[PDB]
Image (cartoon, coloured by chain):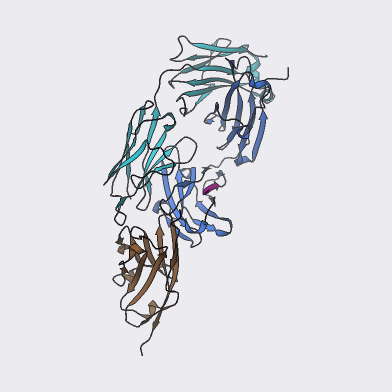
Chain colours: A brown, B blue, C cyan
Amino acid sequence: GSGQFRVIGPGHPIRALVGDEAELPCRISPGKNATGMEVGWYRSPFSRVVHLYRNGKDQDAEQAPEYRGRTELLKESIGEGKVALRIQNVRFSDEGGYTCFFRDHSYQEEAAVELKVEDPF
Amino acid sequence: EVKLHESGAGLVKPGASVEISCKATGYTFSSFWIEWVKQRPGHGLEWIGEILPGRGRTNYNEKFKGKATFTAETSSNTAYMQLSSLTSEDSAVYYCATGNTMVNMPYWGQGTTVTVSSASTKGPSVFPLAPSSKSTSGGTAALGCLVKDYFPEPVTVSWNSGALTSGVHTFPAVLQSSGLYSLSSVVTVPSSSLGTQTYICNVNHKPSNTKVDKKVEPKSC
Amino acid sequence: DIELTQSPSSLAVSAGEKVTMSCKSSQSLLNSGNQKNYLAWYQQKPGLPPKLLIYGASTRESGVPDRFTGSGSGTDFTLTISSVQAEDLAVYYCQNDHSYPLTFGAGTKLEIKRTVAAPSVFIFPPSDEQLKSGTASVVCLLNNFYPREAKVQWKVDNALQSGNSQESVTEQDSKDSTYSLSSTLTLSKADYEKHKVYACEVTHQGLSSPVTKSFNRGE
């Protein structure tokens, strides 16, 4: 009687070469249709909003200016409680922890995710 | 099994600060957003904001930004709200509500009252309203209590701590020209009953600590 | 901010009648992912917190009687009570439960009209404990009546009084839909013992002729 779910992330840091793409996966378990739910990511230090999906649409006017036109939320299997944060033209300033979360009405769990931005050369 | 309870000073001086607290029991306190709602007679409900205990996340209503401030301590499953530079507008009954996976705000605490005023608190005087012949109509008699001169609201009045409920009319307070509140709490019972029944009104006025138990009987004539 | 307009602002019906309440939002309250209108209807009886009847524009909370139904979508919704009940007396608020900042409507108060019922008049003499304290309080109680409008006048030794007694009233009973008024006559111990006959004259629609209930100080 409790849709109360645990949120799960990588479990190990995610790697990416500078100036590249990055994908951060996050899902809820048991998985369920997270289409109506609120999903989002925070950039660890000062909880800046990296990306926010709510009421079916991406809330663009609600993300930190530093991230505009740099993210995306893969929604292929959202009905499975699965999504992924994709980021373009990576930079070191993207190195560090992130925080993903799902809000099921008055319920809301989160998972910590971390990104390693390594230097090619 | 999920249930919230509110509490906090019921009388505070203008331009000061009050911190109403919300205690929650019956669940994993840290994963559900708590809502704070203001309400005052000449108005309906006002949403102030919410808070996710644990994560420590906050969302306030624009108009309450700066006025209100939330926080909580997992240690006690208590969420707090601190209103500042209090005004008469800030005089009302504040609630806190929580929810579940399918609804936000299905659960509401009992709410506590808060009145802003540079005036001082008074303990009630409780004067019994004796059952009598001039109080008996049919095989039914009316007795009761008279809670007088207390400030500010509210007071909670019960009979036999619950061993009585039906026929109990507790009147809405009133503003006496003395600036204090007054109230009568009546309850009708069988003329018969009176002779074997322990009829006691439990008065309570936290804003003063007062907890009086006045037994109301016909006489000792 | 989304604003909610409730109407009628209040209405009165009899037990068993159908009642319909309006709430019209200034914006859409549809979550696209759910394809659901996030609106809620709360019932608020006197004294306790608000009760949640329906969420999502049309879904009943556990326990809530089926006579309650909330329909609508778009910017316009409605709450309907198939067959009103006495205990249904309360205030009904609707609420934008989808966009921040959350907002509630002004509410629609629901009165329960019935037939006439004459006041059970009861008079109370100042306790012995209050006198020792300088002031005197006399209570005249009108028990369970209908309508609400009713005169209650104090006469001391047959002397009409004025601005020396205040009255209080109760919201309708949740079971018989009646009222009860308490007219409290306040005096000084000085003035209390300076007179003989105390009484209140009640004038109500269920009373063929004014009822008077009295006693004589010192009894």
The residue lying furthest to the right in this view is B221
- Image height of B193 relative to C60, above or below: above
Residue B183 placed where, x, y %?
A: 56, 29
Residue B200 placed where, x, y %?
A: 65, 29
Q: Quadrant of residue C24?
A: top left
Q: Is residue B124 visible?
A: no
- Image height of B184 relative to A93, above or below: above
> Closest to the observer: B88 or C175?
C175
Q: Quadrant of residue A14?
A: bottom left
Q: Is residue B155 visible?
A: yes
Q: Is residue B2 magenta?
A: yes
In magenta, the rendered stretch is B1-9
Q: Quadrant of the C terminus of chain B?
A: top right
> Closest to the observer: B175 or C52?
C52
**Residue, x 42% and y 32% (percent of image)?**
C88
The residue lying furthest to the left in this view is C74
State left or right for residue C72 relative to residue C119: left
- Image height of A32 relative to B16, above or below: below
> Closest to the observer: B151 or C103?
C103
The residue lying furthest to the bottom in this view is A121
- Image height of B50 relative to C125, above or below: below
State left or right for residue A25 relative to residue B164: left
Q: Quadrant of residue C164?
A: top right
Residue C73 placed where, x, y %?
A: 28, 46
State left or right for residue A39 relative to residue B108: left
Residue B35 placed where, x, y %?
A: 45, 51
Q: Is residue C208 magenta?
A: no
**Residue, x 45% and y 74% (percent of image)?**
A11
> Closest to the observer: B213 or A33?
A33
